[PDB]
Image (cartoon, rainbow over all chains, first blue to last red; front, top):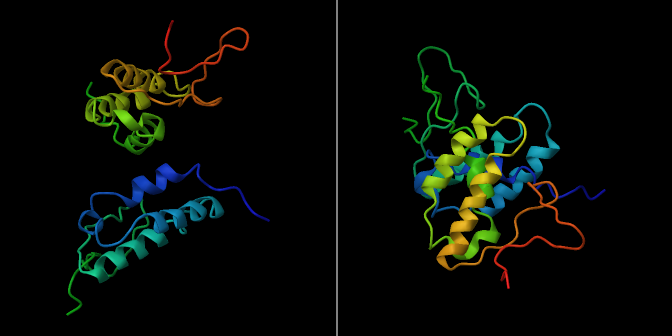
Length: 96
Length: 96
């Protein structure tokens, strides 16, 4: 059944996606599709934020693949990740 | 005591203020000062939205005074206003 257009969470998605760490990709990748995707993601996925931060991850991957370099956005309260030792989770660093 | 910078609601103020109704005044009046004021208003006035819709009212008054004509933004759930009879509330209409 056609659910309501989840436009009540548009501000949250726009604020989260268009942060400082995503500066040098605003001209590489568009924005409308990825935020429209966040629209349904936010309402279709109540409770834990395991379903919204999986889009901005795709936005960052597209950012990195085009040629840009994003900053760090994952905080201890925004879908953090853990690795053993003092290894630091980052974006846009050489795998070598 | 100096309170925390109420930047956690910056997205809310930015979204609500930069709507389509305020189209032809983005070039007349600045944006930073009024949004900065909205920052404290949103966090210093919990519960009812009697402080947030007092700043955008000033933004609209400036929009109209400079020469622009803003659109309607007051909805039935966004600080509505009532007048007796079928007196419709509007912005930028002649008092004559």
